[PDB]
Image: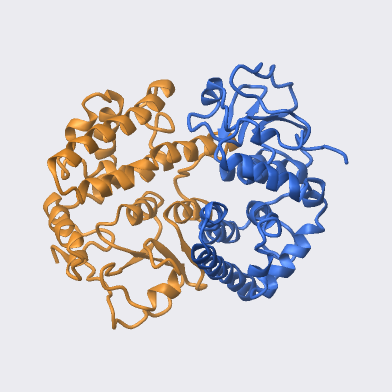
Chain colours: A orange, B blue
Amino acid sequence: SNAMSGESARSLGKGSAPPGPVPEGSIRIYSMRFCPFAERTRLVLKAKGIRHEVININLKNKPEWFFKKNPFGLVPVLENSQGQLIYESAITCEYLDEAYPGKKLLPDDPYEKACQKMILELFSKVPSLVGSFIRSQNKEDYAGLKEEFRKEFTKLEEVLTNKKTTFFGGNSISMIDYLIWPWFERLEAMKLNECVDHTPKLKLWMAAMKEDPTVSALLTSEKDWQGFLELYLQNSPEACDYGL
Amino acid sequence: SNAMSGESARSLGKGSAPPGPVPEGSIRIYSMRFCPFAERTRLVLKAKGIRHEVININLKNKPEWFFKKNPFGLVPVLENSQGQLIYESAITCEYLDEAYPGKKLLPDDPYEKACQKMILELFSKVPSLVGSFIRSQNKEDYAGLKEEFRKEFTKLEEVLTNKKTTFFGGNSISMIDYLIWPWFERLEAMKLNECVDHTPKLKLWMAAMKEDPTVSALLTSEKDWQGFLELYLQNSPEACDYGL
């Protein structure tokens, strides 16, 4: 398969040197191959056809210089040739949509843009629920979390039902779809396919997202992801490079 | 004193008569007189000179119809004559800045606009610390929380230092100052004024904000705030109307 983004780039850990300045005409993304928050930014870069380079950060052995890129020490972080730094996944995505030409991902209409950001807050509980599920130590907690997924997924189903459209912002894929897609991308890998069996519009949306050329170009092995996940929970410095 | 931002409106609770229609050319804000998040929205409405009506919600006796304005059941909520509903304080502020004429509060530059949103994230721990502080009942826990305030205020002082500006978005007042002002406005009332003494530029920004005409027009009694707070902590249905 053709390696996209920074799918083959080994991560930078403790003792790595700070990278050199970003070349003129390019934008750098500090990312992690399996981070859903950094995937939002990689999806936008691909969709808009922005020339970019990827540096992967070993999130379980972070270089001290990374905290100079983002004081929170989290990926994604964008860095341009002027040395400007942009962090927070949603801020990185909105910045790229505004600063570069190509397909316009967010609507200009103030209310429509506000709707995409309100849908993002309707989704906000999913990332921590995904977190609690992966760290689940017994069958009782495990089963209850599946019911929570169904409850949160129903709120998204309601948005699609009212909008009477395939995607969260209309007939075509827009910003909001790319912002929430990295968590749905892993549902099958997490064995959570049953959580969408009472949300038919969201299940059709997932199928339609899998067919998008940008989405499709970034898909990776479900087994590299489970393998990564096992090591990440063990706080392994080898987690972020699993499969390389 | 002269009320120009819903200071005189008794809150609507369970059983109360819901409001009429929103007049054409005006916008409604569902608010609460002492809510710092809804205050961000009131500051933006006043600064831009937007015709608006304030409806206060009794947060400790919430009408069930309010959940149809915002499924989260929180203020602020904007509602126009077309029936569009906008919620989440930061979303309500950006929407008003984009949709209406008057003074521009957010910068035109994509990076400068991204900086405002990253500074809001650097401030994001302050509301939860304020929550914990007001609930503190131990001398050790009281002193400990003050050290955390000092550390969060230092992150804000560093932004002002690096920028060499009076305000968080330049040498003139802008969106970001209004978004964080409602918490600093109350430090004196909470007996936390001394927590800003180690952050000189932050203390001068507080003085400068106090002199802004928009900030000054929304001035309230420190004692009304304190009295409201005691009752709010007791989950009293009389809290939101304190002073009326």
Instruction: Kindly tell me whether residue A189 is visible in this rendering.
Output: yes
* Quarter in which the C terminus of chain B is drawn: top right
Front position in the image: A212 or B170 = B170
In the displayed structure, would residue A164 be above or below residue A3?
A: above
Q: Where is residue B133 drawn, in percent x and y?
A: 55, 56
| Left or right of A216 on screen, residue B141 | right
Left or right: residue A215 compared with residue B16: left
* Residue B205 x, y percent position in the rendering: 72, 65
The answer to which of A189 and B205 lies nearer the viewer is B205
Measuring 45% from the left and 43% from the top, which residue is drawn there?
A105
Q: Is there any visible trace of residue B102 in the rendered image?
A: no
Q: Quadrant of residue A149?
A: top left
Which residue in the rendered view is the most extreme toward the front? B138
Depicted A23 relative to depicted A124: above or below:
below
Quarter of the image where one finds residue A204: top left
| Count of numbered marks | 0
* Residue B230 image point, x, y percent: 63, 44
Q: Nearer the viewer, residue B50 or A113?
A: B50
Percent across and percent down for residue A35 are 29, 56
**Nearer the observer, A27 or B181:** B181
| Residue at figure coordinates x 13%, y 40% from the top left | A139
Q: Quadrant of residue A151?
A: top left
Q: Residue at x 35, y 53 (%)?
A: A37
Residue placed furthest toward the right: B1
Q: Residue at x 26, y 24 (%)?
A: A200
Give above or below for A141 relative to A48.
above
Quarter of the image for the N terminus of chain B: give it: top right
